[PDB]
Amino acid sequence: PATALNTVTAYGDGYIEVNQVRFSHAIAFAPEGPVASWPVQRPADITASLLQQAAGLAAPEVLLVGTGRRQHLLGPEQVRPLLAMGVGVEAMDTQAAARTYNILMAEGRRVVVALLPD
Image 1 (cartoon, rainbow, N blue to C red):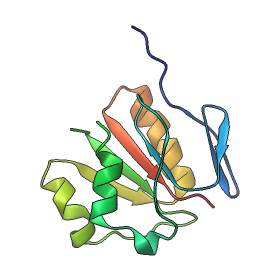
Image 2: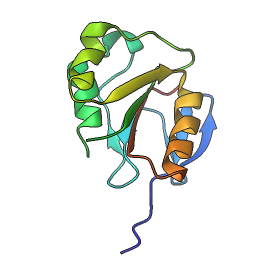
Image 3: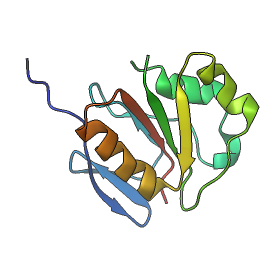
Image 4: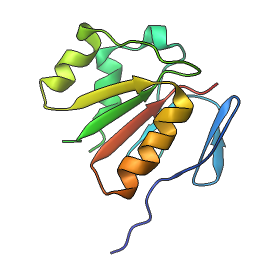
């Protein structure tokens, strides 16, 4: 029916609050579904394999990637498979990723977000 959507509630130094619950480990999620844990810890150990599993939960317009405190450029070997699927990815510091997610979500776009906290 009218399923409630996942919403980034607050952002903090060292945490993202989703649906009023704090997370201090990396997570990934779409508007619908659970807020899943994402096996990453440094923008350095981010792999296309990891990006696809995050996006792999529901085909999505954009995969937002929060690389933590500051933006971290993702390379061709990270991002190509996804484009190979017409999925566009955007890396940016985490507080912006979270905030950009709420927006893309509010205007009803098919969006997934992956975030490394702190």
